[PDB]
Every structure is written in C-alpha cells, then in structure tokens.
Amino acid sequence: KFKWGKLFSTAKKLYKKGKKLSKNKNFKKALKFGKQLAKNL
Image (cartoon, rainbow, N blue to C red; front, side, top):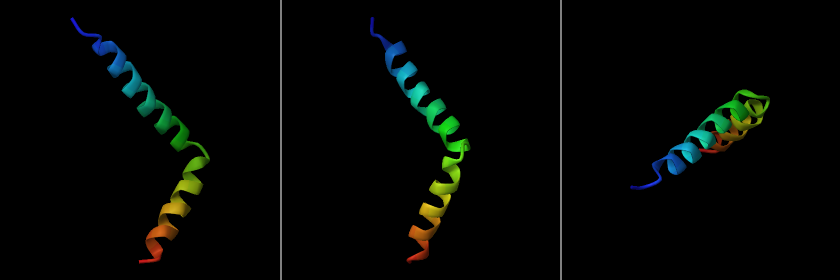
C-alpha cells in the first residue's frame, strides 16, 4: 500500500537525465575536470 512509483520514477528520471546530459558536450568538461583533479596525485 505504498507509492513505490514515486521513488522509481524519480530515480529513473535522475539517471536518464544524468546520462543524456552526460553524453552531451558536458562530457568534455567533466572529463577534463576529473582527469586534472586526478593528475594532481
């Protein structure tokens, strides 16, 4: 008797959004950012 669809929808949305927004040009920035950050060592 719980609204599982709420959590499922929310999570699913964030995931789909993140991916779609990731495959975009944002990937470049995200990549460089992480890379450089790890380069510091």
